[PDB]
Image (cartoon, rainbow, N blue to C red; front, side, top):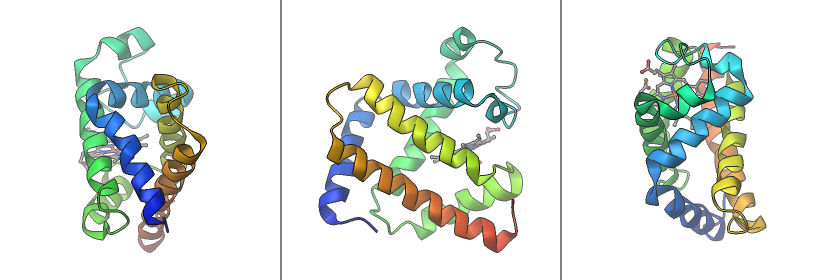
Length: 152
Ligand code: HEM
């Protein structure tokens, strides 16, 4: 549950991401994979990437970064009213991709990390707070659908 003030901050921060969605998406996935190597194993099309340089050079990783952040952005722009958008993601990630909720926590923190890295001094305390709450909301609603499905 975010206030409109907090949503305003979220979408303001998101404007930074949309100015370069591929570059942001790329660094988020790289931060995830290098921070938490077990996550790489969930991607049959990235598990070949043994080094970060290979990750950096991968146009398909950048492409997937775009898909992921485009989806997240569409969800954030709903300001919490995202049941329709979120349910198919929850379902594919529990039933097909088999992504534990822990990894959604991982990528949440990775987003925070990347924003600070790309916008040092331009991602204030209030902005971080709002974005964090937004990602928690996202995660919590996915977690509800996981429980429904009995997925661990
Ligand atoms: C903000 C969080 C995330 C968003 C918005 C997101 C979104 C998406 C979307 C839109 C797709 C393609 C459509 C689909 O299969 O449902 C996808 C595919 C996929 N995602 Fe996620 N995802 C997120 C987090 C994660 C995480 C943390 C992992 C694993 C650590 C993951 C693993 C995968 C895999 C393995 C695929 C299939 C890739 C392929 O084979 O083409 N996702 N994701």
